[PDB]
Length: 278
Length: 278
Ligand SMILES: O=C(O)[C@@H]1[C@H](C(=O)O)NCCN1C(=O)c1ccc2c(ccc3ccccc32)c1
Image 1 (cartoon, rainbow over the protein chains, first blue to last red):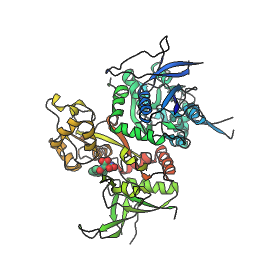
Image 2 (cartoon, each protein chain N blue to C red):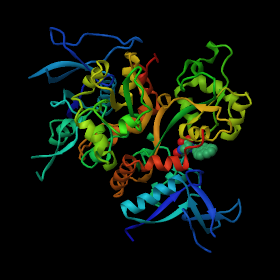
Image 3 (cartoon, rainbow over the protein chains, first blue to last red):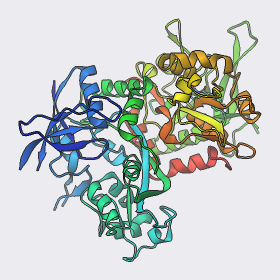
Image 4 (cartoon, each protein chain N blue to C red):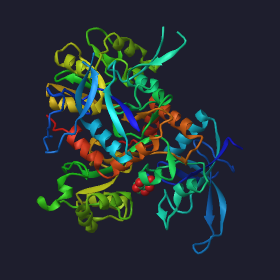
Protein backbone atom coordinates (compact mmCIF):
# COMPACT_ATOMS: atom_id res chain seq x y z
CA UNK A 1 0.00 0.00 0.00
CA UNK A 2 2.85 2.46 -0.78
CA UNK A 3 2.04 4.19 -4.03
CA UNK A 4 4.52 5.76 -6.41
CA UNK A 5 2.81 8.97 -7.52
CA UNK A 6 3.87 10.68 -10.72
CA UNK A 7 3.05 14.32 -11.37
CA UNK A 8 4.25 17.27 -13.44
CA UNK A 9 4.96 20.97 -12.98
CA UNK A 10 1.80 22.86 -13.94
CA UNK A 11 0.66 25.89 -11.93
CA UNK A 12 -1.77 26.26 -10.26
CA UNK A 13 -2.28 22.51 -9.94
CA UNK A 14 1.34 21.67 -9.16
CA UNK A 15 3.97 24.15 -8.02
CA UNK A 16 7.58 22.98 -7.88
CA UNK A 17 10.14 24.76 -5.66
CA UNK A 18 13.66 24.08 -4.31
CA UNK A 19 13.91 22.61 -0.80
CA UNK A 20 15.52 24.56 1.99
CA UNK A 21 19.21 24.02 2.75
CA UNK A 22 18.31 21.28 5.24
CA UNK A 23 16.16 19.52 2.65
CA UNK A 24 12.79 20.38 4.17
CA UNK A 25 10.04 22.54 2.67
CA UNK A 26 9.53 26.13 3.88
CA UNK A 27 6.36 26.46 5.99
CA UNK A 28 3.96 28.83 4.23
CA UNK A 29 0.31 29.89 4.26
CA UNK A 30 -1.93 30.85 1.39
CA UNK A 31 -3.18 34.38 0.84
CA UNK A 32 -6.38 33.37 2.66
CA UNK A 33 -4.54 31.96 5.69
CA UNK A 34 -4.60 28.23 4.92
CA UNK A 35 -1.51 26.12 5.62
CA UNK A 36 0.19 25.14 2.38
CA UNK A 37 0.60 21.36 2.45
CA UNK A 38 3.92 20.53 0.81
CA UNK A 39 5.37 17.12 -0.05
CA UNK A 40 8.87 16.12 -1.08
CA UNK A 41 8.92 15.28 -4.77
CA UNK A 42 12.02 14.03 -6.57
CA UNK A 43 12.57 15.02 -10.19
CA UNK A 44 15.13 16.10 -12.82
CA UNK A 45 17.05 19.29 -11.93
CA UNK A 46 20.29 14.17 -12.44
CA UNK A 47 17.58 13.58 -9.79
CA UNK A 48 17.03 15.81 -6.70
CA UNK A 49 14.42 16.25 -3.96
CA UNK A 50 12.13 19.29 -4.36
CA UNK A 51 8.93 20.69 -2.86
CA UNK A 52 5.55 20.28 -4.57
CA UNK A 53 2.18 21.74 -3.57
CA UNK A 54 -0.99 23.04 -5.20
CA UNK A 55 -4.47 21.89 -6.16
CA UNK A 56 -3.39 18.38 -7.18
CA UNK A 57 -1.16 17.89 -4.14
CA UNK A 58 -4.02 18.82 -1.79
CA UNK A 59 -6.20 16.34 -3.67
CA UNK A 60 -3.54 13.61 -3.25
CA UNK A 61 -3.34 14.21 0.51
CA UNK A 62 -7.10 13.95 0.83
CA UNK A 63 -7.11 10.72 -1.21
CA UNK A 64 -4.20 9.21 0.77
CA UNK A 65 -5.96 10.01 4.06
CA UNK A 66 -9.43 8.80 3.00
CA UNK A 67 -8.34 5.50 1.50
CA UNK A 68 -5.46 4.98 3.92
CA UNK A 69 -2.48 4.65 1.59
CA UNK A 70 1.02 6.04 1.73
CA UNK A 71 2.93 7.54 -1.19
CA UNK A 72 6.15 8.87 -2.60
CA UNK A 73 5.89 11.60 -5.22
CA UNK A 74 8.04 12.12 -8.27
CA UNK A 75 8.01 14.43 -11.28
CA UNK A 76 7.76 12.72 -14.67
CA UNK A 77 11.30 12.25 -16.06
CA UNK A 78 10.63 13.51 -19.59
CA UNK A 79 8.41 16.35 -18.40
CA UNK A 80 5.49 15.38 -20.67
CA UNK A 81 1.85 14.48 -20.09
CA UNK A 82 1.87 11.58 -22.54
CA UNK A 83 1.05 10.60 -26.12
CA UNK A 84 1.45 7.32 -28.00
CA UNK A 85 4.14 7.14 -30.65
CA UNK A 86 5.53 4.61 -33.13
CA UNK A 87 8.91 3.24 -32.05
CA UNK A 88 11.55 3.23 -34.81
CA UNK A 89 8.22 0.34 -36.29
CA UNK A 90 5.33 -2.01 -35.44
CA UNK A 91 5.34 -1.31 -31.69
CA UNK A 92 3.69 1.81 -30.23
CA UNK A 93 4.80 3.29 -26.89
CA UNK A 94 3.49 6.00 -24.57
CA UNK A 95 5.82 8.74 -23.34
CA UNK A 96 5.32 11.14 -20.41
CA UNK A 97 3.26 10.33 -17.33
CA UNK A 98 1.24 7.83 -19.35
CA UNK A 99 4.40 5.85 -20.08
CA UNK A 100 5.58 5.86 -16.48
CA UNK A 101 2.20 4.65 -15.27
CA UNK A 102 2.03 1.89 -17.89
CA UNK A 103 5.61 0.70 -17.26
CA UNK A 104 5.13 0.60 -13.48
CA UNK A 105 7.50 3.49 -12.67
CA UNK A 106 4.35 5.04 -11.18
CA UNK A 107 1.19 3.55 -9.66
CA UNK A 108 -1.00 6.60 -10.01
CA UNK A 109 -0.94 9.86 -11.96
CA UNK A 110 -2.03 12.86 -9.89
CA UNK A 111 -1.84 15.87 -12.19
CA UNK A 112 -4.09 17.92 -14.47
CA UNK A 113 -4.32 14.92 -16.80
CA UNK A 114 -6.90 15.27 -19.60
CA UNK A 115 -9.36 12.39 -20.02
CA UNK A 116 -9.62 11.23 -23.65
CA UNK A 117 -10.46 8.14 -25.67
CA UNK A 118 -6.84 7.50 -26.69
CA UNK A 119 -5.61 7.19 -23.12
CA UNK A 120 -8.72 5.52 -21.68
CA UNK A 121 -8.00 2.56 -23.98
CA UNK A 122 -4.95 1.64 -21.84
CA UNK A 123 -5.57 3.12 -18.39
CA UNK A 124 -8.39 3.74 -15.94
CA UNK A 125 -9.42 7.34 -15.22
CA UNK A 126 -11.35 8.50 -12.18
CA UNK A 127 -14.47 10.59 -12.66
CA UNK A 128 -13.27 14.14 -13.39
CA UNK A 129 -11.87 16.07 -10.46
CA UNK A 130 -11.96 19.23 -12.59
CA UNK A 131 -14.19 20.25 -15.53
CA UNK A 132 -12.66 22.71 -17.93
CA UNK A 133 -11.74 22.95 -21.59
CA UNK A 134 -9.45 24.29 -24.28
CA UNK A 135 -8.92 27.96 -25.01
CA UNK A 136 -6.34 30.28 -26.59
CA UNK A 137 -3.85 32.66 -24.97
CA UNK A 138 -2.55 35.77 -26.74
CA UNK A 139 -0.76 39.01 -25.84
CA UNK A 140 -3.27 41.76 -25.06
CA UNK A 141 -3.91 43.68 -28.26
CA UNK A 142 -3.62 40.57 -30.42
CA UNK A 143 -6.84 40.07 -32.36
CA UNK A 144 -8.22 36.62 -33.17
CA UNK A 145 -11.84 35.47 -32.88
CA UNK A 146 -10.69 32.06 -31.75
CA UNK A 147 -10.18 28.59 -33.14
CA UNK A 148 -11.86 29.42 -36.49
CA UNK A 149 -9.93 32.61 -37.13
CA UNK A 150 -8.56 32.60 -40.69
CA UNK A 151 -5.07 33.17 -39.25
CA UNK A 152 -5.48 29.82 -37.50
CA UNK A 153 -7.43 27.99 -40.18
CA UNK A 154 -5.15 29.15 -43.02
CA UNK A 155 -1.72 29.29 -41.35
CA UNK A 156 1.49 31.02 -42.43
CA UNK A 157 4.74 31.91 -40.64
CA UNK A 158 3.47 35.48 -40.21
CA UNK A 159 1.26 34.30 -37.31
CA UNK A 160 2.66 31.52 -35.15
CA UNK A 161 0.60 29.35 -32.85
CA UNK A 162 1.43 26.19 -30.93
CA UNK A 163 0.55 23.95 -28.03
CA UNK A 164 2.61 21.70 -25.78
CA UNK A 165 4.40 18.70 -27.35
CA UNK A 166 3.18 15.24 -26.41
CA UNK A 167 0.00 16.44 -24.66
CA UNK A 168 -3.73 15.89 -25.05
CA UNK A 169 -3.88 19.04 -27.19
CA UNK A 170 -1.34 17.50 -29.57
CA UNK A 171 -3.56 14.38 -29.71
CA UNK A 172 -6.64 16.57 -30.32
CA UNK A 173 -5.23 18.28 -33.41
CA UNK A 174 -3.52 15.14 -34.72
CA UNK A 175 -6.60 12.88 -34.54
CA UNK A 176 -8.73 14.78 -37.10
CA UNK A 177 -7.79 14.81 -40.79
CA UNK A 178 -9.66 18.12 -41.28
CA UNK A 179 -7.24 19.64 -38.75
CA UNK A 180 -4.17 18.39 -40.64
CA UNK A 181 -3.36 21.85 -42.00
CA UNK A 182 -3.39 23.35 -38.50
CA UNK A 183 -1.39 20.43 -37.13
CA UNK A 184 1.28 20.82 -39.80
CA UNK A 185 1.78 24.39 -38.61
CA UNK A 186 1.76 23.56 -34.88
CA UNK A 187 4.22 20.65 -34.96
CA UNK A 188 6.80 23.04 -36.40
CA UNK A 189 6.35 25.22 -33.31
CA UNK A 190 5.12 23.13 -30.34
CA UNK A 191 6.82 23.86 -27.01
CA UNK A 192 8.39 21.51 -24.44
CA UNK A 193 6.23 22.78 -21.57
CA UNK A 194 3.30 25.12 -20.85
CA UNK A 195 5.50 27.57 -18.94
CA UNK A 196 7.88 28.03 -21.90
CA UNK A 197 5.01 28.60 -24.34
CA UNK A 198 3.46 31.14 -22.01
CA UNK A 199 6.76 33.00 -21.68
CA UNK A 200 7.14 32.98 -25.45
CA UNK A 201 3.77 34.68 -25.84
CA UNK A 202 4.98 37.41 -23.45
CA UNK A 203 8.20 37.75 -25.44
CA UNK A 204 6.27 37.95 -28.71
CA UNK A 205 8.00 34.81 -30.04
CA UNK A 206 4.68 32.91 -30.09
CA UNK A 207 1.46 34.62 -31.18
CA UNK A 208 -1.11 32.18 -29.79
CA UNK A 209 -0.85 29.34 -27.28
CA UNK A 210 -3.61 26.72 -27.39
CA UNK A 211 -4.03 25.05 -24.00
CA UNK A 212 -6.14 24.08 -20.94
CA UNK A 213 -8.43 26.87 -19.79
CA UNK A 214 -7.98 25.97 -16.13
CA UNK A 215 -4.33 26.92 -16.70
CA UNK A 216 -4.65 29.78 -19.21
CA UNK A 217 -7.22 31.75 -17.21
CA UNK A 218 -5.08 31.50 -14.12
CA UNK A 219 -2.11 32.81 -16.12
CA UNK A 220 -4.07 35.73 -17.61
CA UNK A 221 -5.20 36.77 -14.13
CA UNK A 222 -1.63 36.79 -12.83
CA UNK A 223 -0.20 38.43 -15.93
CA UNK A 224 -2.34 41.24 -17.35
CA UNK A 225 -0.37 41.57 -20.60
CA UNK A 226 -1.90 38.17 -21.44
CA UNK A 227 -5.54 37.45 -22.31
CA UNK A 228 -7.56 34.48 -23.44
CA UNK A 229 -9.82 34.67 -26.47
CA UNK A 230 -12.90 32.79 -27.74
CA UNK A 231 -14.09 31.13 -24.50
CA UNK A 232 -13.86 27.33 -24.64
CA UNK A 233 -13.82 25.70 -28.05
CA UNK A 234 -13.80 22.24 -26.54
CA UNK A 235 -14.76 20.86 -23.14
CA UNK A 236 -12.77 18.22 -21.28
CA UNK A 237 -11.93 17.09 -17.75
CA UNK A 238 -8.94 16.10 -15.64
CA UNK A 239 -8.95 12.79 -13.82
CA UNK A 240 -6.68 10.63 -11.67
CA UNK A 241 -4.95 7.96 -13.79
CA UNK A 242 -4.42 4.34 -12.71
CA UNK A 243 -3.57 1.03 -14.38
CA UNK A 244 -6.61 -1.09 -15.18
CA UNK A 245 -5.87 -3.50 -12.33
CA UNK A 246 -5.72 -0.91 -9.54
CA UNK A 247 -7.61 -1.95 -6.37
CA UNK A 248 -7.96 1.78 -5.64
CA UNK A 249 -10.06 2.63 -8.70
CA UNK A 250 -13.56 2.57 -7.28
CA UNK A 251 -12.68 4.37 -4.04
CA UNK A 252 -10.71 7.12 -5.74
CA UNK A 253 -13.74 7.87 -7.92
CA UNK A 254 -16.14 7.74 -4.98
CA UNK A 255 -13.84 10.09 -3.05
CA UNK A 256 -13.77 12.60 -5.90
CA UNK A 257 -17.56 12.55 -6.23
CA UNK A 258 -17.93 13.02 -2.48
CA UNK A 259 -15.47 15.91 -2.56
CA UNK A 260 -17.38 17.74 -5.30
CA UNK A 261 -20.59 17.24 -3.31
CA UNK A 262 -19.34 18.44 0.10
CA UNK A 263 -17.50 21.58 -1.00
CA UNK A 264 -13.96 20.25 -0.78
CA UNK A 265 -13.34 20.86 -4.50
CA UNK A 266 -14.93 24.29 -4.09
CA UNK A 267 -12.34 25.05 -1.41
CA UNK A 268 -9.48 23.90 -3.64
CA UNK A 269 -10.68 25.93 -6.61
CA UNK A 270 -10.96 29.04 -4.41
CA UNK A 271 -7.50 28.50 -2.94
CA UNK A 272 -5.62 27.70 -6.12
CA UNK A 273 -7.64 28.19 -9.31
CA UNK A 274 -9.94 31.18 -8.74
CA UNK A 275 -8.83 34.63 -9.76
CA UNK A 276 -9.63 38.35 -10.01
CA UNK A 277 -10.18 39.60 -13.57
CA UNK A 278 -7.74 42.33 -14.71
CA UNK B 1 -30.19 -12.78 -26.56
CA UNK B 2 -26.85 -11.60 -25.11
CA UNK B 3 -26.72 -8.70 -27.58
CA UNK B 4 -30.27 -7.47 -27.02
CA UNK B 5 -30.49 -5.11 -24.04
CA UNK B 6 -33.31 -4.02 -21.75
CA UNK B 7 -32.89 -0.25 -21.41
CA UNK B 8 -34.85 2.13 -19.19
CA UNK B 9 -35.37 5.85 -19.71
CA UNK B 10 -37.57 8.65 -18.40
CA UNK B 11 -39.66 11.30 -20.12
CA UNK B 12 -37.98 14.67 -19.75
CA UNK B 13 -37.88 17.12 -22.68
CA UNK B 14 -35.56 17.90 -24.41
CA UNK B 15 -33.48 14.93 -23.25
CA UNK B 16 -36.26 12.40 -23.81
CA UNK B 17 -39.47 13.37 -25.58
CA UNK B 18 -42.36 10.91 -25.80
CA UNK B 19 -44.91 10.86 -28.62
CA UNK B 20 -47.79 8.64 -29.70
CA UNK B 21 -47.21 6.06 -32.44
CA UNK B 22 -48.53 6.85 -35.94
CA UNK B 23 -49.11 3.53 -39.41
CA UNK B 24 -48.44 1.52 -36.21
CA UNK B 25 -44.71 2.42 -36.32
CA UNK B 26 -42.12 4.93 -35.10
CA UNK B 27 -40.65 7.08 -37.85
CA UNK B 28 -38.33 10.06 -38.38
CA UNK B 29 -35.79 10.43 -35.58
CA UNK B 30 -37.89 8.51 -33.05
CA UNK B 31 -37.41 4.98 -31.71
CA UNK B 32 -39.89 2.54 -30.11
CA UNK B 33 -40.29 2.79 -26.34
CA UNK B 34 -42.98 1.18 -24.24
CA UNK B 35 -44.70 2.36 -21.09
CA UNK B 36 -46.55 0.36 -18.46
CA UNK B 37 -49.65 2.54 -18.11
CA UNK B 38 -51.74 2.25 -14.93
CA UNK B 39 -55.45 1.46 -15.07
CA UNK B 40 -56.17 3.98 -12.32
CA UNK B 41 -54.46 5.64 -9.34
CA UNK B 42 -55.40 3.00 -6.74
CA UNK B 43 -54.02 -0.15 -8.29
CA UNK B 44 -50.92 -1.99 -9.48
CA UNK B 45 -52.89 -3.05 -12.58
CA UNK B 46 -51.76 -1.63 -15.91
CA UNK B 47 -51.09 -2.21 -19.61
CA UNK B 48 -47.99 -1.93 -21.77
CA UNK B 49 -48.45 0.78 -24.35
CA UNK B 50 -46.32 1.36 -27.43
CA UNK B 51 -44.83 4.84 -27.75
CA UNK B 52 -42.12 6.70 -29.68
CA UNK B 53 -39.17 8.45 -28.04
CA UNK B 54 -36.73 11.04 -29.33
CA UNK B 55 -34.41 13.69 -27.92
CA UNK B 56 -30.82 14.41 -26.89
CA UNK B 57 -30.43 11.18 -24.88
CA UNK B 58 -32.20 9.10 -27.53
CA UNK B 59 -29.76 10.34 -30.19
CA UNK B 60 -26.94 9.31 -27.81
CA UNK B 61 -28.52 5.87 -27.41
CA UNK B 62 -28.77 5.55 -31.19
CA UNK B 63 -25.07 6.37 -31.59
CA UNK B 64 -24.08 3.91 -28.88
CA UNK B 65 -26.24 1.16 -30.40
CA UNK B 66 -24.53 1.66 -33.79
CA UNK B 67 -20.98 2.03 -32.45
CA UNK B 68 -20.98 -0.57 -29.66
CA UNK B 69 -23.21 -2.87 -31.76
CA UNK B 70 -26.10 -3.81 -29.49
CA UNK B 71 -29.83 -3.88 -30.02
CA UNK B 72 -32.30 -2.75 -27.35
CA UNK B 73 -35.79 -2.82 -25.92
CA UNK B 74 -36.45 0.63 -24.54
CA UNK B 75 -39.02 1.34 -21.81
CA UNK B 76 -40.05 4.34 -19.73
CA UNK B 77 -39.80 4.05 -15.96
CA UNK B 78 -43.15 4.20 -14.14
CA UNK B 79 -42.28 4.05 -10.46
CA UNK B 80 -40.35 7.22 -9.66
CA UNK B 81 -38.19 9.46 -11.80
CA UNK B 82 -34.40 9.38 -11.86
CA UNK B 83 -33.93 7.47 -8.61
CA UNK B 84 -34.30 8.03 -4.86
CA UNK B 85 -33.75 5.59 -1.99
CA UNK B 86 -37.05 5.26 -0.12
CA UNK B 87 -37.17 2.85 2.86
CA UNK B 88 -33.77 1.61 1.68
CA UNK B 89 -35.29 0.67 -1.67
CA UNK B 90 -34.18 2.44 -4.84
CA UNK B 91 -36.94 3.67 -7.13
CA UNK B 92 -36.85 5.31 -10.57
CA UNK B 93 -34.28 4.58 -13.28
CA UNK B 94 -31.63 3.75 -10.70
CA UNK B 95 -33.95 1.10 -9.21
CA UNK B 96 -34.54 -0.60 -12.57
CA UNK B 97 -30.78 -1.03 -12.96
CA UNK B 98 -30.03 -2.04 -9.35
CA UNK B 99 -32.77 -4.67 -9.40
CA UNK B 100 -31.64 -5.99 -12.80
CA UNK B 101 -34.70 -5.05 -14.83
CA UNK B 102 -32.59 -2.87 -17.08
CA UNK B 103 -29.04 -3.33 -18.30
CA UNK B 104 -28.68 0.42 -18.50
CA UNK B 105 -30.43 3.69 -17.91
CA UNK B 106 -30.26 6.60 -20.31
CA UNK B 107 -31.63 10.04 -19.56
CA UNK B 108 -30.86 13.21 -17.64
CA UNK B 109 -29.39 11.10 -14.87
CA UNK B 110 -26.99 13.00 -12.60
CA UNK B 111 -23.82 11.20 -11.43
CA UNK B 112 -23.35 11.27 -7.66
CA UNK B 113 -21.66 9.38 -4.80
CA UNK B 114 -24.81 7.82 -3.36
CA UNK B 115 -25.92 6.29 -6.70
CA UNK B 116 -22.36 5.28 -7.56
CA UNK B 117 -22.40 2.95 -4.57
CA UNK B 118 -25.09 0.86 -6.25
CA UNK B 119 -24.62 1.35 -10.01
CA UNK B 120 -21.65 2.05 -12.24
CA UNK B 121 -21.73 5.24 -14.31
CA UNK B 122 -20.32 5.93 -17.75
CA UNK B 123 -18.14 9.00 -18.20
CA UNK B 124 -20.23 12.21 -18.09
CA UNK B 125 -21.74 13.14 -21.46
CA UNK B 126 -23.25 16.49 -20.36
CA UNK B 127 -21.76 18.79 -17.73
CA UNK B 128 -23.95 19.88 -14.83
CA UNK B 129 -23.79 20.96 -11.20
CA UNK B 130 -25.41 23.59 -9.04
CA UNK B 131 -25.69 26.86 -10.91
CA UNK B 132 -27.47 30.20 -10.52
CA UNK B 133 -29.78 32.08 -12.89
CA UNK B 134 -30.40 35.81 -12.67
CA UNK B 135 -31.87 38.61 -14.74
CA UNK B 136 -29.04 40.40 -16.62
CA UNK B 137 -27.56 43.13 -14.46
CA UNK B 138 -27.85 41.25 -11.17
CA UNK B 139 -24.38 40.58 -9.75
CA UNK B 140 -23.48 37.27 -8.06
CA UNK B 141 -20.91 34.56 -8.42
CA UNK B 142 -21.94 30.99 -7.71
CA UNK B 143 -23.50 29.23 -4.73
CA UNK B 144 -20.55 30.04 -2.43
CA UNK B 145 -20.90 33.83 -2.77
CA UNK B 146 -21.11 35.52 0.66
CA UNK B 147 -24.24 37.26 -0.67
CA UNK B 148 -25.84 33.81 -0.52
CA UNK B 149 -24.03 32.49 2.56
CA UNK B 150 -24.66 35.58 4.69
CA UNK B 151 -27.44 37.56 2.94
CA UNK B 152 -27.90 39.89 5.93
CA UNK B 153 -24.38 41.26 5.44
CA UNK B 154 -25.73 43.08 2.35
CA UNK B 155 -28.37 45.70 1.58
CA UNK B 156 -30.90 45.12 0.34
CA UNK B 157 -30.71 41.44 1.27
CA UNK B 158 -30.83 39.09 -1.71
CA UNK B 159 -33.99 37.14 -2.49
CA UNK B 160 -33.13 33.66 -3.82
CA UNK B 161 -34.64 30.22 -3.81
CA UNK B 162 -34.78 26.78 -5.34
CA UNK B 163 -37.35 24.03 -5.92
CA UNK B 164 -38.06 22.16 -2.67
CA UNK B 165 -37.36 18.43 -2.31
CA UNK B 166 -34.75 18.05 -5.03
CA UNK B 167 -30.99 17.53 -5.11
CA UNK B 168 -30.09 21.21 -5.13
CA UNK B 169 -32.02 21.81 -1.89
CA UNK B 170 -30.54 18.64 -0.43
CA UNK B 171 -27.03 19.78 -1.24
CA UNK B 172 -27.59 23.26 0.18
CA UNK B 173 -29.06 21.78 3.37
CA UNK B 174 -25.85 19.77 3.85
CA UNK B 175 -23.36 22.46 2.90
CA UNK B 176 -24.82 25.84 3.91
CA UNK B 177 -27.30 25.35 6.74
CA UNK B 178 -28.17 29.02 7.26
CA UNK B 179 -28.54 29.65 3.54
CA UNK B 180 -30.92 26.71 3.35
CA UNK B 181 -33.01 28.05 6.20
CA UNK B 182 -32.99 31.51 4.58
CA UNK B 183 -34.19 30.26 1.19
CA UNK B 184 -37.23 28.39 2.44
CA UNK B 185 -39.49 31.44 2.18
CA UNK B 186 -38.37 32.09 -1.41
CA UNK B 187 -38.66 28.59 -2.78
CA UNK B 188 -40.48 27.94 -6.05
CA UNK B 189 -43.08 25.35 -7.09
CA UNK B 190 -41.10 24.56 -10.22
CA UNK B 191 -38.69 25.89 -12.83
CA UNK B 192 -41.42 27.70 -14.79
CA UNK B 193 -42.67 29.62 -11.76
CA UNK B 194 -39.06 30.50 -10.90
CA UNK B 195 -38.45 32.05 -14.32
CA UNK B 196 -41.52 34.26 -13.93
CA UNK B 197 -40.44 35.31 -10.44
CA UNK B 198 -37.10 36.39 -11.86
CA UNK B 199 -38.67 38.21 -14.84
CA UNK B 200 -41.26 40.02 -12.71
CA UNK B 201 -38.66 41.07 -10.13
CA UNK B 202 -40.12 39.04 -7.27
CA UNK B 203 -36.89 36.99 -7.06
CA UNK B 204 -33.24 37.99 -7.62
CA UNK B 205 -31.70 34.56 -8.19
CA UNK B 206 -32.78 31.01 -8.80
CA UNK B 207 -30.42 28.20 -7.81
CA UNK B 208 -30.71 24.91 -9.69
CA UNK B 209 -29.20 22.19 -11.93
CA UNK B 210 -26.78 23.79 -14.37
CA UNK B 211 -27.82 21.93 -17.51
CA UNK B 212 -31.48 22.79 -16.92
CA UNK B 213 -30.70 26.47 -16.30
CA UNK B 214 -28.46 26.68 -19.40
CA UNK B 215 -31.27 25.18 -21.45
CA UNK B 216 -33.75 27.73 -20.10
CA UNK B 217 -31.40 30.71 -20.56
CA UNK B 218 -30.91 29.64 -24.17
CA UNK B 219 -34.60 30.12 -24.94
CA UNK B 220 -35.65 33.04 -22.73
CA UNK B 221 -37.92 35.44 -24.68
CA UNK B 222 -35.87 38.66 -24.61
CA UNK B 223 -32.62 36.92 -23.70
CA UNK B 224 -32.45 38.78 -20.37
CA UNK B 225 -32.19 35.66 -18.17
CA UNK B 226 -28.62 34.49 -17.75
CA UNK B 227 -26.52 31.97 -15.75
CA UNK B 228 -23.17 32.47 -14.02
CA UNK B 229 -20.04 31.35 -15.85
CA UNK B 230 -19.33 27.63 -15.83
CA UNK B 231 -16.21 28.32 -13.84
CA UNK B 232 -18.45 29.06 -10.87
CA UNK B 233 -20.68 25.98 -10.96
CA UNK B 234 -20.72 24.29 -7.51
CA UNK B 235 -20.39 20.51 -7.11
CA UNK B 236 -19.58 20.04 -10.79
CA UNK B 237 -20.61 16.65 -12.16
CA UNK B 238 -22.38 15.31 -15.26
CA UNK B 239 -25.28 13.31 -16.61
CA UNK B 240 -24.13 9.78 -17.31
CA UNK B 241 -25.44 6.38 -18.31
CA UNK B 242 -26.06 4.04 -15.39
CA UNK B 243 -25.11 0.38 -15.80
CA UNK B 244 -25.21 -2.56 -13.41
CA UNK B 245 -22.20 -2.81 -11.15
CA UNK B 246 -19.45 -4.83 -12.85
CA UNK B 247 -21.26 -4.62 -16.21
CA UNK B 248 -19.46 -6.01 -19.28
CA UNK B 249 -20.72 -3.05 -21.34
CA UNK B 250 -19.18 -0.21 -19.34
CA UNK B 251 -15.75 -0.03 -20.99
CA UNK B 252 -17.20 -0.03 -24.52
CA UNK B 253 -19.84 2.58 -23.61
CA UNK B 254 -17.17 4.77 -22.00
CA UNK B 255 -14.79 4.60 -24.94
CA UNK B 256 -17.60 5.36 -27.40
CA UNK B 257 -18.82 8.34 -25.40
CA UNK B 258 -15.26 9.75 -25.30
CA UNK B 259 -14.82 9.17 -29.02
CA UNK B 260 -18.12 11.01 -29.64
CA UNK B 261 -16.89 13.94 -27.52
CA UNK B 262 -13.51 13.82 -29.25
CA UNK B 263 -15.03 13.91 -32.75
CA UNK B 264 -17.34 16.84 -31.98
CA UNK B 265 -20.44 14.68 -32.35
CA UNK B 266 -21.44 15.59 -28.79
CA UNK B 267 -21.19 19.30 -29.54
CA UNK B 268 -23.43 18.61 -32.54
CA UNK B 269 -26.15 16.98 -30.44
CA UNK B 270 -25.98 19.87 -27.98
CA UNK B 271 -26.44 22.42 -30.78
CA UNK B 272 -29.36 20.37 -32.10
CA UNK B 273 -31.24 19.82 -28.82
CA UNK B 274 -29.88 22.00 -26.02
CA UNK B 275 -28.50 25.22 -27.46
CA UNK B 276 -31.16 27.90 -27.91
CA UNK B 277 -31.30 31.22 -29.73
CA UNK B 278 -29.82 33.23 -26.81
O1 LIG C 1 -30.25 15.82 -10.21
C1 LIG C 1 -31.43 16.27 -10.29
O2 LIG C 1 -31.78 17.18 -9.50
C2 LIG C 1 -32.43 15.74 -11.32
C3 LIG C 1 -31.88 14.59 -12.13
C4 LIG C 1 -31.44 13.42 -11.34
O3 LIG C 1 -30.47 12.73 -11.74
O4 LIG C 1 -32.01 13.08 -10.27
N1 LIG C 1 -30.76 15.08 -12.98
C5 LIG C 1 -31.21 16.22 -13.85
C6 LIG C 1 -31.91 17.26 -13.03
N2 LIG C 1 -32.90 16.68 -12.25
C7 LIG C 1 -34.31 17.07 -12.48
O5 LIG C 1 -35.16 16.52 -11.78
C8 LIG C 1 -34.88 18.04 -13.49
C9 LIG C 1 -35.65 19.13 -13.09
C10 LIG C 1 -36.18 20.00 -14.04
C11 LIG C 1 -35.96 19.79 -15.42
C12 LIG C 1 -35.21 18.71 -15.80
C13 LIG C 1 -34.95 18.45 -17.16
C14 LIG C 1 -35.47 19.30 -18.13
C15 LIG C 1 -36.25 20.41 -17.76
C16 LIG C 1 -36.75 21.25 -18.78
C17 LIG C 1 -37.52 22.35 -18.46
C18 LIG C 1 -37.79 22.64 -17.12
C19 LIG C 1 -37.29 21.81 -16.12
C20 LIG C 1 -36.51 20.67 -16.44
C21 LIG C 1 -34.67 17.82 -14.84
